[PDB]
Amino acid sequence: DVERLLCQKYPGLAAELQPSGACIIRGVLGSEDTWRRLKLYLPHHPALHGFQLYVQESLEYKLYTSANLKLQDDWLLEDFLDHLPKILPREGNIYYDILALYKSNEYCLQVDEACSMIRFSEFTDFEQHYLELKIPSLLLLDHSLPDCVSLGEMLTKSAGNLEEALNLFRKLLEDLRPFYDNFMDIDELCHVLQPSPISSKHKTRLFPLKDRVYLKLTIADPFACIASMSLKIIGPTEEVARLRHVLSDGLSNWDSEMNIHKNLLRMFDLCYFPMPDWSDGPKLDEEDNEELRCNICFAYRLDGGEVPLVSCDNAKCVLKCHAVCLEEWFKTLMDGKTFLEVSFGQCPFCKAKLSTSFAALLND
Ligand SMILES: OC[C@H]1O[C@H](O[C@H]2[C@H](O)[C@@H](O)[C@@H](O)O[C@@H]2CO)[C@H](O)[C@@H](O)[C@@H]1O
Ligand SMILES: [Au+]
Ligand SMILES: [Au+]
Ligand SMILES: [Au+]
Ligand SMILES: [Au+]
Ligand SMILES: [Au+]
Ligand SMILES: [Au+]
Ligand SMILES: [Au+]
Ligand SMILES: [Au+]
Ligand SMILES: [Zn+2]
Ligand SMILES: [Zn+2]
């Protein structure tokens, strides 16, 4: 309807309606030699009067009402938009600054040819982390840290010179040690199945709790490590059902003076998590049916390191599956309604109960 006109003529605007018969348009409107950040309130869409335009003049938003700004008596939204852009009214040296930072025991600083970009790395106590900026922009290129962090935004607003940038970054690193430290133990003492290749960026970890039962740890806010912590039990219906109670209790009894790993051991009454060990002897014995490969894709490991973990309650149904290879089945089954309303579906193979706890492997 209106996002139509917004799509063809204004790709940088987002028209959000309200059930309150109103309409808010935010986004960017542009002319050939200028653009503005914009927020337009329209109390009476499609009538313009009573309009409330917020244009970012610099640091703050400037407000335009009918008193502020004068429209035409006949204009519609379109008219108002393609008209709007015309009606609205020591410095130190960076190369020196690089040389200033070049030598240091706390990080190696690398300069690209033509010095178009620089890269900090091998940070002390965070040797895995790195930061790349454009020169002399100081525009954020690549970097470690979960992608959900608004580092770019932080830099532009809070970092004036190269040194200020470096430090803002090392600041977050310190802020992030609890997040990182916490995954330290889980990575070394648990058998982490996904992410296949673990990186400074991943806010997640999936590992086995016991035979047939996986536990997926996920940390929404890397700065609010435990506040944003979240556990999900994945496995056969009854195991899931059973363990879900343990989980609740475990959280209620959370020992704040213990990290997540040890707190999980506490939670599930284990002195250690299941993990491959030389003491398992040589496998061979058992020779799990040669087919551990999905069973739909006929692949074992996907381009993203996904692995066949899905399995019905029926011990006798040899047959596993990548969650994504079954993504629709999981959504066409439990569409909307929560998984306690829908615990399972039918094993498309033996018909057995198939826990919908696996849908948890989706999305991410
Ligand atoms: O007798 C089995 C085994 O128990 C312990 O080994 C554990 C190990 O501590 C963990 O990594 C766990 O995930 O699996 C291993 C095998 O059960 C003992 O430490 C080990 O010496 C012993 O053989
Ligand atoms: Au568009
Ligand atoms: Au709208
Ligand atoms: Au140098
Ligand atoms: Au280096
Ligand atoms: Au984030
Ligand atoms: Au934590
Ligand atoms: Au033990
Ligand atoms: Au359907
Ligand atoms: Zn698959
Ligand atoms: Zn089955």
Image (cartoon, grey):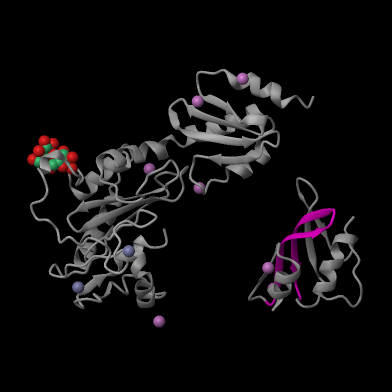
Question: Residue 88, can we see it?
Answer: yes
Figure quadrant of the C terminus: bottom left
In percent of the image, x 10 and y 44: which residue is there?
A: 282
Task: Give x and y (percent) for residue 305.
Answer: 35, 53
Residue situated in front as seen by the camera: 255 or 353: 353
Task: Give x and y (percent) for residue 178.
Answer: 41, 37
On screen, 172 above or below 355? above
Question: Secondary structure of the magenta portion, mostly?
Answer: strand
Quadrant of residue 166 in the image? top right
The reply, left or right, for residue 86 in relation to residue 357 is: right
Task: Give x and y (percent) for residue 23.
Answer: 70, 72
In percent of the image, x 56 and y 41: which residue is there?
A: 142
Check if residue 28 falls in the magenta segment.
yes
Task: Give x and y (percent) for residue 163.
Answer: 63, 27
In percent of the image, x 30 and y 38: which residue is there?
A: 185
On screen, 16 above or below 98? below
Figure quadrant of the N terminus: bottom right
Check if residue 152 falls in the magenta segment.
no
Quadrant of residue 324 in the image? bottom left
The reply, left or right, for residue 254 in relation to residue 86 is: left
The reply, left or right, for residue 173 in relation to residue 345 is: right
Total numbered badges shown on the rendered structure: 0
Question: Residue 68, can we see it?
Answer: no
In percent of the image, x 63 and y 76: which residue is there?
A: 19
Where are the magenta residues, as a range? Answer: 21-44
Residue situated in front as seen by the camera: 59 or 129: 129
